[PDB]
Amino acid sequence: QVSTQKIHYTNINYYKDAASNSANRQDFTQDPGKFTEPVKDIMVKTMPAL
Amino acid sequence: QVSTQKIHYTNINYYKDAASNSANRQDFTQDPGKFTEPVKDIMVKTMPAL
Amino acid sequence: NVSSLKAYQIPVQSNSDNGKQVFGFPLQPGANNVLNRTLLGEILNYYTHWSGSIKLTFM
Amino acid sequence: LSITTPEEMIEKAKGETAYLPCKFTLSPEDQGPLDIEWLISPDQVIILYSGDKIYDDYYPDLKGRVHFTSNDLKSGDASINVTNLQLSDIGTYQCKVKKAPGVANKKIHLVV
Amino acid sequence: SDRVRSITLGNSTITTQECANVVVGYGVWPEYLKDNEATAEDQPTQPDVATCRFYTLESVQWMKNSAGWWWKLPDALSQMGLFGQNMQYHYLGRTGYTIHVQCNASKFHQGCLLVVCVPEAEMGCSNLNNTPEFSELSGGDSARMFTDTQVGESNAKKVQTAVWNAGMGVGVGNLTIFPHQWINLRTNNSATLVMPYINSVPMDNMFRHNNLTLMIIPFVPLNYSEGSSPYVPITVTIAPMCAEYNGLRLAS
Amino acid sequence: SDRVRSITLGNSTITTQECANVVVGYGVWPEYLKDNEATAEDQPTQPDVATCRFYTLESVQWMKNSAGWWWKLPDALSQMGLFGQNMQYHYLGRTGYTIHVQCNASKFHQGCLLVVCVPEAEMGCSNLNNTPEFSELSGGDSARMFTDTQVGESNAKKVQTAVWNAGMGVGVGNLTIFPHQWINLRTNNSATLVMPYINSVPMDNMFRHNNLTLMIIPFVPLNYSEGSSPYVPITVTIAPMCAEYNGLRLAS
Amino acid sequence: ARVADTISSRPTNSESIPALTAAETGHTSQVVPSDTMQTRHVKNYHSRSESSIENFLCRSACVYYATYTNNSKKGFAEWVINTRQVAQLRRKLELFTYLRFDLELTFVITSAQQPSTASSVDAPVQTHQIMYVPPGGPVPTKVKDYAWQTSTNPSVFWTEGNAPPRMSIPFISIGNAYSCFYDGWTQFSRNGVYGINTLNNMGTLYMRHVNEAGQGPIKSTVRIYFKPKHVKAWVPRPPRLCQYEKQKNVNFSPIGVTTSRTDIITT
Amino acid sequence: ARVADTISSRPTNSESIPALTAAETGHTSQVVPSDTMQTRHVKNYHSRSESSIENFLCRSACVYYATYTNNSKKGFAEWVINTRQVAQLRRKLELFTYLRFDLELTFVITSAQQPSTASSVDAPVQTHQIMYVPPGGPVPTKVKDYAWQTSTNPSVFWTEGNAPPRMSIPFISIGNAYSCFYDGWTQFSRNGVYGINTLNNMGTLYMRHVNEAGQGPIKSTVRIYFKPKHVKAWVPRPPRLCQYEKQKNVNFSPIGVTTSRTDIITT
Amino acid sequence: VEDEYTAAGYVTCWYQTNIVVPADVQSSCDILCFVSACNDFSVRMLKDTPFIRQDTFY
């Protein structure tokens, strides 16, 4: 209901749907490992690759 | 006063009548047994009907 | 048979040769003109999407 | 509404019977009444289909020589059969179908 | 060591002496359909030994003036044994592939391939208002080939085969965002990918919708001196993993 | 009650209002191949939903001067869907059948059938020194019929179709030692048998060896007065139970 | 309010037949697809929310629209409140026999200039008055009258360029539910009209301008919109097939059951 | 959601080489600048907030605009809802293959007077009606028709001089995500059009005036604005390089990779 | 509505055996056919029906 901004702010849901809420804008998560290293055997930085 | 939507939402009644409230939209109950099986002797699925 | 009570009957006669067809229709319960005006078809023509299975009681 | 191939080239010989296809499918929003035209520009209408009845006396040079093919025009058939092809039948033919809220064209170039 | 692999499946076995690591999808492994995700109302069939084996497509000759090749993936396996027969009698079906492509040259040839597996590859027609037909878009176990020259306007229904646009109107340098590997004749010999089921619906028909596309594009062309062997073939092998079907009907 | 049955399998369902009890083999139920009995060195495949369903053969007209019919059992199902396609690409395979035969008349017709399932039914040729060919011994989903008259000597390769010897040189009255049931239009309507895998080897090829034979012989012939329906058809439905295969190869 | 799931099954062969039944007893069968084939255990996550009554009926629909000229004598619009005149809403009401609901009346009022003759016309913003008369009250005859103002009937005053006006009306009836159909006369001698009930009378609506004729006639137009809420329905009814013809009775012309096809096996 | 920092380093000389690698394995290298030189320990306070999906897509953009004349027959605008017609928004959508979002439709309606002939024209404030038809419903043909009012399709009524109207639309699809691309036909015989899907149909929009032709024709113009929220994207895709040409297919004309320079060493 | 992407196949009905009948009974028997939904039926996206037209107020 009350959370921090980018101090706090107060957000109340009014309508009784789910598509009526405002945009979230605060879904801060990332995981680049499924694009950079999509391999089976794991790979270390320091050792040679082959 | 506060309930869930389809997260929560807050609903306040303002006018002092009963016909002034908003629509409920959340009366979720059903009982099809009074249309499908309106018979006196009960009927099992597995056994033959007669 | 559309302006009669004959539209609900399927004629089944003692055939001479074997392996013949009785009827047939596609299963579009809001689009075909056989399952259109039934009690199920006049509920589905108030909505847009449907799901689930359909029972077909014969007698 | 969408036609299979909105332009092509058809090459036939004189005295033969041309077959100008016009097929389509139906998107789910299309619920209005049907309308089918055909044009020529050697912008004169040569046949019509509206209100379930055919009107086909429109072009004097092609009087009684063009007909629809199928009996099931509300299933995606709008092809016509041009009988007794002559040298003066050179021009782009335009199959205009309009079932609301959709509209599509097909410019058929016929060269004999 | 770290150079040899030996992947086996069913009653076949693919072995490689010189190959790099294997790249697997977007980080997931192809598993069966869980019960939370399913929507069909009957019980599926899982042959699991009759389909999961390495089918082998036709081979292509890598000339000096080559352009590229592509295959549509649940269409090249339409005639390959019990996978091609379970695909016709059923109606649904999900798959996961294990693509393997191999091309060998000596220590004296030079060149480099790019092996990518593109999901939902819509291709462009020659004329701007038409759409390409089925016979000119894919072939049963036969590679359709790119060109190095723009296809002329006089064709009615032909695929635009300009290789620097990769057929889809996109820059070919940016194609590495998909799961991919490089064949390089200096240090590598065989490329291998594992592709899970990527579709917006949990199951799909297989005759109307080719939901993968394996493209092979040579960036550095093949080059050698006189006296070396001039014929260098490429050969791709694909094996479906964890397939299942639904909805029996007649043949078609 | 005790008269209705409802046997279902896969995506089909056979229901009967008036039928007698079911007779099952020599007292065993068709189960899978245990690991003590197996001899093949690879892993079998079990489709189990794509094969286990009730296929329906053609029908035959029961005239007044009828003789009998027979089917060779792992040969009538050679063209019936995914069973007929897994039988061609493989090499081995064991099955267990669930035979069902149905023939309805009113309360005014009279007659009686005998439904028997004979294992290893070798039949006799017309000439004493020849052997019957394949095209005159069985048919794909079509019943070969007996006669009431001894086949002449002028034929080269034809089956001896004398019904009182049942084709095999044996008395037809002693045929009830095999698992069998009677169709009798007075009190019965449908016969049903369950046959396990009966062979001297744990698995067998299916194109060279028909290891069952379903015979149908009318003892009391059909008879009625004028005014009743004259066309009485018989229709048999067979469903394989707990099938499995081995040994992939090419098509044949 | 989730739907029921489906449980897996095994190939049975026994005496308990779930498929054979008898429809003579008026009992629609309650079989599951897990009884005639082999199914898998499907987690089912659909919802029957939008099929409820309070999501099927609580939507606004036009009921009537009347026009009235400012520069006229007896320029004003009267309308007895009844659902029977439109057809897209009426067919939704006759699915059930006895209904019970309150109401949210909403008006959308637009104006248009008539081809006047005077020079350099200009008018300020207009004012409309929508008077609601319960059944029995004194009604006005001409527009310039003192029965419009000096009354305790609940009216609403509206000027243009704002949000549309909206009033709410509770369940005003003498019985316990509105009767959509009434088989039987209203006079004890059984003479006269057939299906006329005095159980769903709600009153009339009188609408007029408030300003005067400045220089140019203005012809307005007002639509009326229902919105039933808190609705409870009883005793369902098969849907109307033939076309409506009158607002009071239920009379019709005969027509076939459905549109035809060519042959009984044609797909 | 801060970015990673950088740690200091010392001059090494050993066997562990972090810079040499092999790009054959499809593995983009994960080196840090602390491995090829000497760095200082930098406290890093940047943020990756504005690069997220819900800050990249949730911005309003025009999709279509149509004009319609008050003084006409069939003066009204129909438009099937699809993203494919503008180009500044379409290129942002084809970065991902499967999208899933709700929608906040917003309309900006303006009006203009046509060169009429009548004398001393004056009109009050206008009223517009924006009707939304789900795929399958009955659509209107002429403007003066009873299918506009007497319907339960969700429409919105708006008068000029106020805030612009706005309605919200949830995720209306049959699959689990909108398909931006569909390689494969829609008919099982594999004939006909190529990339036509029935997975992202949202319906049409019918807009018209509510007033009548008083004295002078008014030609209006209405823009439509999307706003995707709660967006989840899947399976990214390289961005479109060549120009668009059609709204349904993906066809194009070939062009080079980039603009050229004079020589390979020219800076 | 009639779409090609989500068609639902066909339902046919075939003679297994004939309809046999004794003497002095009519032959052409008739068959009725019902339709209904299961316990897990569901709908969505309420629209207005195409079956009822109008051109005036009654």
Image: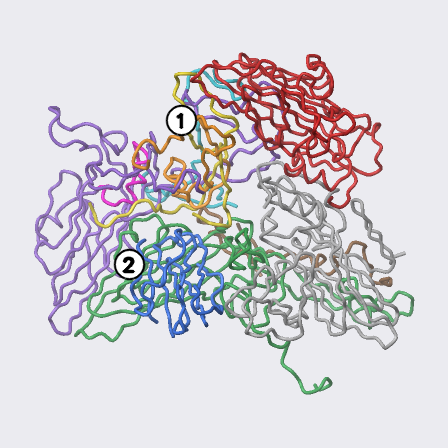
Chain colours: A brown, B cyan, C orange, D blue, F red, G purple, H green, I yellow
Q: How far apart are labels 2 and 1 at the CA level?
A: 48 Å
Total numbered labels: 2
Q: Is residue G55 left or right of residue F173?
A: left
Label 2 belongs to which residue? H142
- Looking at the rendering, which quadrant does residue G125 occupy? bottom left
- Image: D20 above or below F168: below
- Type of residue at label 1? Asp
Question: Closest to the observer: C32 or C48?
Answer: C32
Q: Chain of mark 1?
A: I
Question: Residue at coordinates 38% horizontally, 47% vertically from top-left?
Answer: I47
Question: Closest to the observer: G238 or G14?
Answer: G14
- Looking at the rendering, which quadrant does residue H132 occupy? bottom left
Q: Chain of mark 2?
A: H
Label 2 residue SS = loop
Question: Closest to the observer: G180 or I57?
Answer: I57
Q: Is residue B3 left or right of residue A7?
A: left
Residue range corresponding to the magenta coloring: G82-102
Label 1 belongs to which residue? I30
Q: Position of residue G189 (x, y in %)?
A: 11, 24
Label 1 residue SS = strand
Q: Is residue C18 left or right of residue G145?
A: right
Q: Is residue F206 left or right of residue D32?
A: right
Asked whether G97 falls inside the magenta stretch, the response is yes
- Mark 2, Cα crowd under 10 Å, few <14 / some 14-19 / many 20+, is few
- Judge depth for marks 2 and 1 and give the one in front: 1
Asked whether H49 falls inside the magenta stretch, the response is no
